[PDB]
Length: 273
Image (cartoon, rainbow, N blue to C red; front, side, top):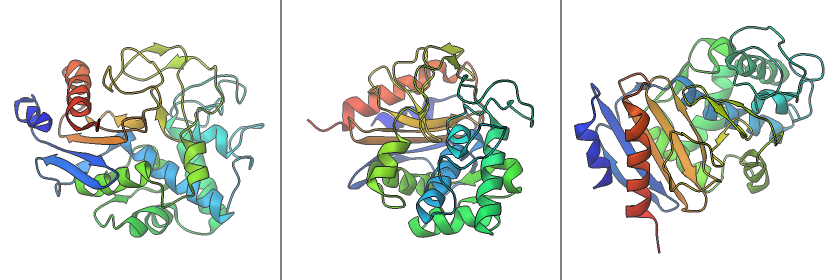
């Protein structure tokens, strides 16, 4: 019932799914429809980088980006790298600043060290193993931070992997969902300065940020990502629930109250006693 609120949303089109450890608990809209993911691309690339670490292709401490920066800094947005270009604006690990280019350097490292084109690496390491046959990233590492395309059905499967890790070990997933470089403050695009602005290994961590895109009832351990294309994904380890929402309207003030509302509606209705 909670997902029905989508029919009243001021968007050209939308689709959503509630996922639990046993599978999809509810859906709405066309789950087969392809949507631009924008930054919802990051969790996919992050998982691919996590698989690469486990394959031994790279290590979390492997140098990548500005001097003193590593794969871990790139994943957690602490490389000191600028938002859009190879401009070093801070010393690695001192500041937390969301960066698209940070993910391109990340994709470039995995690509170089593995010998596989990143888009293809993503497919073979994440999408193919989970059956995500309508998910793709074209554009190479330059678009590693926002160029992925997918469907609610494919993301639903992905959310399953985030709830019960299979593509990576339970230890890597625990690590990826733990705050990396804690204590760092910063702005969460669209939600202003956050103290602190916690981030995991490629996955944003809610903590107690406010205002935020998740619900007021999501636990502080909730992690995921939203995108400027008007889509998002969060996984709440405490509620053991996941929510995927994709719309055809770019992020804006219209979503500021709706996103949190559907999140709390979903938690209240599907959270097991």
